[PDB]
Amino acid sequence: GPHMATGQDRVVALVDMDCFFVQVEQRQNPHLRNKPCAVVQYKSWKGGGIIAVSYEARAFGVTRSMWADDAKKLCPDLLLAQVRESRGKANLTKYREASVEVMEIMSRFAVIERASIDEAYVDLTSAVQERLQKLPISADLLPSTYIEGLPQGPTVQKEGMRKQGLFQWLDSLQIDNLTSPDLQLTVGAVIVEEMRAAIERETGFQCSAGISHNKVLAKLACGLNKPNRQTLVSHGSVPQLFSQMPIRKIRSLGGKLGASVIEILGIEYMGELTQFTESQLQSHFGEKNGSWLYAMCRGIEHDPVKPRQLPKTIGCSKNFPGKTALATREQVQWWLLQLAQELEERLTKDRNDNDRVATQLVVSIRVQGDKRLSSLRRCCALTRYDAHKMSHDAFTVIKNCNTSGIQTEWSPPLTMLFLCATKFSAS
DNA sequence: ATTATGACGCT
DNA sequence: AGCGTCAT
Ligand SMILES: Nc1ncnc2c1ncn2[C@H]1C[C@H](O)[C@@H](CO[P@](O)(=S)OP(=O)(O)OP(=O)(O)O)O1
Ligand SMILES: [Ca+2]
Image (cartoon, helix red, strand yellow):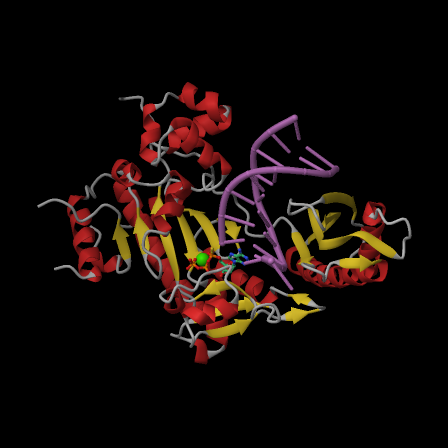
């Protein structure tokens, strides 16, 4: 009771851009706005692989990982934008630069953790304290906010439902104590409305957001009312929310571990985890995972928002599927050079922008016949930002992977090359 | 023949 | 270090 931690100490938000590469292309090309459209990379094999889909196109069943030719079967009027090709490969610079636009705006409000190209966590605990001292919260301050779990108790069109939930929530708020976690989340949501308004004003991009007491709940919250809306998941909302929430929906449980939780414990939903002792969960899933699961199923998580706005690595990779697999030494060296020249370009820009230098080069390849995504990974020193040097260095660290007796040929053929700059130091 | 990324845990 | 897992 009196000593029972409730994980209500922080206000954390997760901001997730909607259909982000699509929005980047729609900003650039007005003709794509408010249309079923997708972003595709390459075009020769089956029309290209889809990596992003507008919500209009999702209504037809178009998804990521679909070939454009097949998506066209579902949606004949589907519009497509192609990822830039440079030096023979897809080049994601446009989307990395758009990401920086959003991340810099978010950083005006609080220190962010860059989670992916279009997602960032923010710890709003301090900003909420400040806003609290400056002030009753009007519904007008929360025009795109859902309160998860509401309305409840004794019209039915979506905006009506949203407002009815929001009204129940605000009506229940004890606003006179500056210590109420629910009030803190609410003020957090007011700030996120402001952040999201600024992102849209200043970039043209819309996004969704979750507000809760930790990163995992904020992330879960965010997805509950995509797109262009934000969702508040209170501590009190967790038992009902988790009672029907498949374990795989929770960040880090969407893979083998999550499947093992389901299989070993014979459960389906996050809420069912509460019936196990911490020691029981540790016994099955290890010390760290077990403690993490015990707290998480009660809505409690302690992973901090890390103050990191920049990626920790800068990498360049290309697959050579089917019989495009690299079988000659000339081929291997040409493509290592292409990758190295892109890497050099991005590295030089990074050093100018961000006052840092990578010190380690990681070289990864895949060989035809291997089932793993990476067959072999070797590091060497990265001492100069020089593409010819990096490509030569990469070749020497992998050249003995060639089982071919003659060194004019490469065997078994390479189906992936990967160069990654790591271990940055200030400069 | 999804591809091109990127963070973090394990030993 | 090199490899595996999990995620955009
Ligand atoms: N598997 C994969 N390969 C390549 N690029 C990807 C992949 N997944 C996502 N992305 C890119 C393209 C996306 O626009 C961008 C962000 O991914 P996410 O957030 S999973 O999806 P979005 O396109 O932003 O739609 P959504 O967030 O509104 O659901 O990363
Ligand atoms: Ca997104």
